[PDB]
Image 1: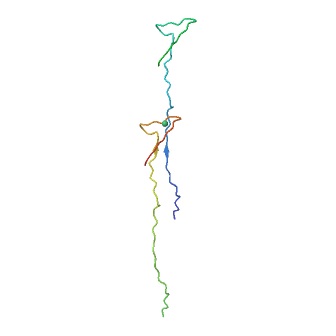
Image 2: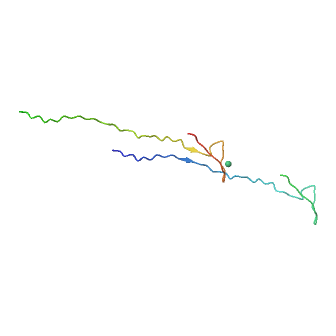
Length: 49
Length: 49
Ligand SMILES: [Ca+2]
């Protein structure tokens, strides 16, 4: 009578949500406060973070 | 008188009910919980059962 269609199934799901990286920024204001930059001046400025 | 029609019978029956196999499935959610998948990421996921 019944000629079974021999076909069973298995399934799965994958969730890719985020991007690998977050670039958190703290911008710099290099002449800063309690220091001074002059025209034609020479030197170095550094922000560690 | 009676000319016996010499024909006796034997019979039998066979019961084919089930299909050979049962594919029980536990689907996978591969990023899972307490783990994370990122875009462009590389690695391995495994489900034992
Ligand atoms: Ca990885």
